[PDB]
Image (cartoon, coloured by chain):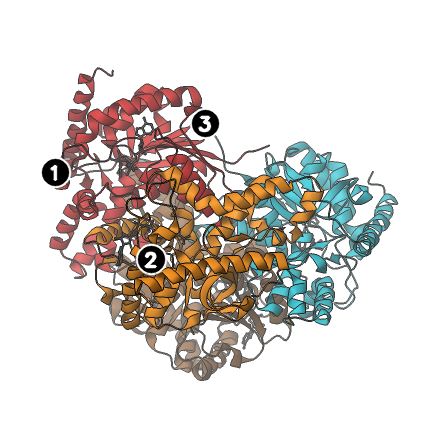
Chain colours: A cyan, B brown, C red, D orange
Amino acid sequence: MTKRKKISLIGSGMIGGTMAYLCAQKELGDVVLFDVVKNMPQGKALDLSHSSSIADTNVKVTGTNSYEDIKGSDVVIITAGLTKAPGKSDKEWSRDDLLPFNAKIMREVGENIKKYCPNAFVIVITNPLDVMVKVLHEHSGLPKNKVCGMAGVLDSSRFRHFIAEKLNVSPRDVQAMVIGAHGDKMVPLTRYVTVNGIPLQEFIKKGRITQEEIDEIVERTKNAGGEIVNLLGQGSAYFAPAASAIEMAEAYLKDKKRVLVCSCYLEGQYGHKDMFVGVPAVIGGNGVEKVIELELTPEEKELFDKSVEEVRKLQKAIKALGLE
Amino acid sequence: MTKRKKISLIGSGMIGGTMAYLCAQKELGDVVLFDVVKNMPQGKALDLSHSSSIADTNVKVTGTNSYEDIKGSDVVIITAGLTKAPGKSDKEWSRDDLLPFNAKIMREVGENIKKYCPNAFVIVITNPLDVMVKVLHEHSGLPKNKVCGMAGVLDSSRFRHFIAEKLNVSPRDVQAMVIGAHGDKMVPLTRYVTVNGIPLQEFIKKGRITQEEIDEIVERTKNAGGEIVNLLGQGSAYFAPAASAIEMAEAYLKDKKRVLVCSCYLEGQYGHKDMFVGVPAVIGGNGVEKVIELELTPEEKELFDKSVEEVRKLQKAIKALGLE
Amino acid sequence: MTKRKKISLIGSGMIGGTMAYLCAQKELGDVVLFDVVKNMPQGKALDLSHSSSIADTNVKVTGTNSYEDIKGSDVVIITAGLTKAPGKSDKEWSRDDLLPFNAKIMREVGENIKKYCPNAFVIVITNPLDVMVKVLHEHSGLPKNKVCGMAGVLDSSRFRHFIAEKLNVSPRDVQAMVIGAHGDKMVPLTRYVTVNGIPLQEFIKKGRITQEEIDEIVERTKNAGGEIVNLLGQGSAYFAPAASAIEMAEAYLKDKKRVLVCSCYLEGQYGHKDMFVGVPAVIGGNGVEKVIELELTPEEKELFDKSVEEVRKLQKAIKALGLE
Amino acid sequence: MTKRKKISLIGSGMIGGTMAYLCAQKELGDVVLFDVVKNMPQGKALDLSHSSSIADTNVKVTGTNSYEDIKGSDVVIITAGLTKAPGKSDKEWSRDDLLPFNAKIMREVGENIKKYCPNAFVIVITNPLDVMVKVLHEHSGLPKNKVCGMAGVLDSSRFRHFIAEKLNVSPRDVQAMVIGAHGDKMVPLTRYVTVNGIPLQEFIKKGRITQEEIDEIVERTKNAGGEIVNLLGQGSAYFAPAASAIEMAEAYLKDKKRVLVCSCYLEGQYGHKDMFVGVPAVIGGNGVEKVIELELTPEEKELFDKSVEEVRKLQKAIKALGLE
Ligand SMILES: NC(=O)C1=CN([C@@H]2O[C@H](COP(=O)(O)OP(=O)(O)OC[C@H]3O[C@@H](n4cnc5c(N)ncnc54)[C@H](O)[C@@H]3O)[C@@H](O)[C@H]2O)C=CC1
Ligand SMILES: NC(=O)C1=CN([C@@H]2O[C@H](COP(=O)(O)OP(=O)(O)OC[C@H]3O[C@@H](n4cnc5c(N)ncnc54)[C@H](O)[C@@H]3O)[C@@H](O)[C@H]2O)C=CC1
Ligand SMILES: NC(=O)c1ccc[n+]([C@@H]2O[C@H](COP(=O)([O-])OP(=O)(O)OC[C@H]3O[C@@H](n4cnc5c(N)ncnc54)[C@H](O)[C@@H]3O)[C@@H](O)[C@H]2O)c1
Ligand SMILES: NC(=O)c1ccc[n+]([C@@H]2O[C@H](COP(=O)([O-])OP(=O)(O)OC[C@H]3O[C@@H](n4cnc5c(N)ncnc54)[C@H](O)[C@@H]3O)[C@@H](O)[C@H]2O)c1
């Protein structure tokens, strides 16, 4: 009587397929790979189905161009949209140039979620992340706690990796957060970086790392997306983005109460409301179950507010289109 | 001081990166992504490094364009090559058309394995699989038991998947083997298909599956690679090929004594010698530890011989190109 | 909101605690450890809770002496009862001697399952297995397909282990089944043993194993439980029994459609009905979804019938106790 | 040529067996279960071998009464000892009471490690922990960095569990350390407790947890071992101790560079030397690679010094017994 969890991946591109692969490997549930491109998602679904046999896991992987197949989905993860705006080089790529392109897609997707799986937990990945999640939320009519954006987990995992590498410790034992908008005004929280709860400052004071190296890592974290785009030559990152979204999905599916930075609907926290922005949150069976309001210093609070200001800017541009 | 296992991936494209992802997820050991394309492997290595942080695993992922970095690898997995021959068409995709382009790449890679990592266990993926592994082996100087080709695990995973699908059981509990050349004359062994050891014939007698349905599944298995190419539009399968090769690498790294079908150097088994072709084998810490010689019926033996003949015919082309 | 799966373990002894540990490690769901012994399950639940933190899993483990706490359990696994009959030596240890003691306990548990979690999938472990599961089913009023006994997965795992050990191959690649009653008259199906679908017979001919060795392995499988008892000195096996029951529980919870040998309610299969006996079955979200009827030879069929008669002998003793 | 890792467990009791189970589930390497009791480890090894087949893992489990079988071990984990001093009661259970019984055992074990596997990484569990590891180290001749005691990971996991429970978040996201002696004077470092790097102090201010609740948890953490002893009625904890020890073993075997609190040989850190005591350490392929010196406050430093003093006093008892 109790069926497997159902996870619909709206967008079967690099990140879409990669998330499906994680689902197959982890046996998270049945997977629906949706895309507007004909044949391709069916192709990937076949490949993934074969991969599940190798993994000795029990997972149906379905490729589709029909929104009807997302019916009854427990989780929906959205990557539909463009990665690199047309006519832009590698060394000038920006998430903000995509807004006119991707906003209309979020409406169509939101509308379809509304009628096929209105009780799904929905994770948005499409850029510009923080406004795309807002557009999705509006047109889907979903509860504020059942929709969020993936960015913070990815930005934070990068911050963690860079710190872990410099200190030569397991990234499991580094805690680091990046809050705010997903972009150049993201706010890596150096003051909150710990090694198993030990303040990063203790490693400074002990000369395991210098403040200047920390400053460089902060900058590298902010630019990490572009760094990868430049090195690859084609497209952008997808391994860590896929893993990031699936960590959020697992938190929901198994009611884990993970503390993860996600793009969450604010209802007054940090003195802001009516937008999604990167904040630490408790993720569980009820979606975004809690937004944690950090005791930011005035300096930190100003960086966050400037970050939120960027989102506000894009939001008007969205308003000057016609997507409620 | 016992270091982590070191796995070098020669070729950092679709399958290479995907394999590196599994290594990160599974914490198999440190990964070197080698490619001739500048910067791209470094870019992917960054993305994969970030994903390892998310996975809470402890894995070093290095992107490189220098064969020196493969020194002392425990396992080397080779994907270097073209996926589709230049100037060809989708429905006309053939593994054989890659022979003249990929043959010389196998010579180059072999020469470099010879000098930098002669003690590695080497898994070849590059198509056309069975002759590519021969070129690699010949030019690398490695022992016969330390080189093999990934094909049988993938072909068998497909055969298993389709059987499991039709019978509606877990693929874990379906045993199916495909032997011979990795191409149109591969031999799906219907007589050897079992469900937890229960012969497929019992399911036929009990009317759970028909001979006609089995026949369709046999042909579908043969055409699976091309089916995916036609659907994907760009490139060929990579999720299952990646998983297959890593299953083989795991068998070596942890001396598992897995029974896997791989392209192995024959020394009289099945009445054939001095070529690589798909056969059931025991894989462990000594590489291809044992080729299993199945009690084939005359009909099966003839199918196998015709399969081997295709490898011999491809070999004539290798010889005529002057690639040994 | 969707809650985590809930698994109630009725009996918190060795097997009970061990299953709880697997649950914590695998994050299968929240665990309730029930026992009539005061304080002990609370103590184990604390210990296990700490182990879940170490494992980075998200699992509540609750020890209890009250049946109310099994409310809403998705799976119930029952180990309540004695392991050894009082006034019996190890060399005379017999599962049959546990009957009058454990029969009455199965009645109580079934009554409590009826009122507290009538929709659970129930796995009985308590000996004498095949008749204990019938008692439990009778007094629980549960559907025939939602109750079964763990025995065949354990007996088969032993058969597999001993075969794999002799052939020196991965137990993953050995398929072996033991059907019939869980006792001296269990039936290890030598004819159905395969190595990745390859009949064991081929390895006899190829000289990797002899019929004499196989015969001795059959005997060792039958005696495996008593062999461990004699070696241990106190109680009986628990690591493999726990793992066997959890494998069954996982098949249900994730609707895997695994082919596992379990003690299942027969309704005409093999020419028998209205008793539980070990047979191959497909386990999924609807419990015992299908009982597979093997094409046993007359000789095999006679061994199985003899096995079934042993269950009937025990059953008649149950009738004596005046418990319907 | 490259063999599986080899892990020897000196002591095949509750914790020994449980650790072997984890090795089997995780496929960490082959396992030797050593004990002075005849037949018992052989019995457990069989049970565990069967469970490996169920897990589809590839692990040899060997029971023995001969030290010769621990030769070539990569890791050795020692649980040889009594759990409760004879003549004593549960409520008055004290690890210190075990000293005169287990000290001579550590000498015996140490002597045998000296001659059979001097190159192993050795983890001691036997109580009283901090002085038992010292006796073992003294009589084994091993390097200072290749020997340590399991305590801090367990104490910390308990601290973590209790904090995570109260705040209703995943224990993955709670960082908490307990340093010092493994006993009543252990030091749960409240100041260093974080939720993904967020200081616990913020949660106090935001009214998510009270100082009173924290004080209770600190006491509960100190008393946790005795709490379980009282509840179980027999023996002491084993699920979490086994897991803690395996976490340490994994960190070594795969060179993970984990930050874990372990009883480590001090050489001037914190102002102390030549004793083992619980401190944060980096564990990797070189064993105890680094002892981290925390910037303790003067109050915290006093607690730690008082904790170290307890070890010194236990050490006085060792010398008085005639065990150096
Ligand atoms: N069953 C099987 O055996 C399968 C085989 N394949 C084969 O695997 C190969 C790779 O497939 P994908 O990873 O999808 O292709 P891909 O095109 O994504 O990656 C191939 C990579 O090899 C690199 N390369 C080219 N020359 C090289 C050299 N001399 N040394 C090192 N690297 C070099 C390229 O720069 C490219 O990044 C193809 O030959 C394909 O036919 C693919 C799927 C299944
Ligand atoms: N946090 C910690 O450090 C913890 C420490 N412990 C300690 O771990 C030790 C073992 O606990 P359990 O496994 O539960 O006890 P157990 O009584 O179940 O097993 C102890 C085993 O050691 C064996 N043994 C005795 N003398 C020996 C010798 N000379 N050589 C080899 N083996 C010998 C016994 O035969 C017995 O099987 C105890 O000393 C206990 O106090 C237990 C829990 C947590
Ligand atoms: N931190 C982050 O949030 C993060 C990280 C990486 C990428 N991204 C973003 O995620 C998105 C996906 O990236 P990718 O690498 O998978 O790109 P991709 O080009 O590989 O995938 C996009 C897919 O969406 C499909 N698509 C386009 N319009 C659609 C519609 N109306 N309905 C359904 N599908 C449609 C395309 O056919 C394509 O397959 C991009 O917008 C990218 O900017 C975000
Ligand atoms: N193949 C198999 O099916 C298989 C394998 C191993 C053991 N077993 C059987 O499984 C059972 C459990 O074995 P074990 O090693 O866990 O024994 P154990 O003695 O360690 O555990 C039995 C537990 O059941 C409890 N109990 C007794 N009456 C109860 C009641 N009315 N309600 C709740 N709990 C009650 C006891 O207090 C004890 O904690 C035994 O009957 C044994 O014969 C079966």
At label 2, the amino acid type is: Asn
Question: Mark 2 near mark 3, Cβ–Cβ under 8 Å?
Answer: no
Which residue carries the number 2 mark? D58
Q: Helix, strand, or loop for circle 3?
A: helix
10 Å neighbourhood of mark 2: few (<14), some, or many (≥20)?
A: many
Residue in the foreground of this view, choosing between D309 and B165: D309
> Where on the picture, by quarter, is residue D149?
bottom left
Give neighbour class at mark 1: few <14, some 14-19, many 20+ (Cα, 10 Å).
few
Is A163 displayed left or right of D146 in the figure? right
Left or right: where does residue D67 sit relative to residue B114? left
Q: Which mark is residue D147?
A: none
Q: State left or right for residue A220 relative to residue C63.
A: right
Q: Nearer the viewer, residue B14 or C184?
A: C184
Instruction: Residue A125: give x, y in percent of width and height.
Output: 68, 50
Cα–Cα gap, marks 2 and 1: 33 Å
Label 3 crowd bin: few (<14), some (14–19), many (20+), radius 10 Å: some
Q: Are marks 1 and 3 on the same chain?
A: yes
For mark 2, name the chain. Answer: D
Instruction: Determine which residue is flagged by label 1.
Output: C92
Give how far apart the Cα atoms at labels 1 and 3 are: 38 Å
Horizontally, residue C96 falls left or right of residue A284, namely: left
Whether labels 2 and 3 share one chain? no
Q: Residue type at mark 3?
A: Asp
Q: Are marks 2 and 1 on the same chain?
A: no
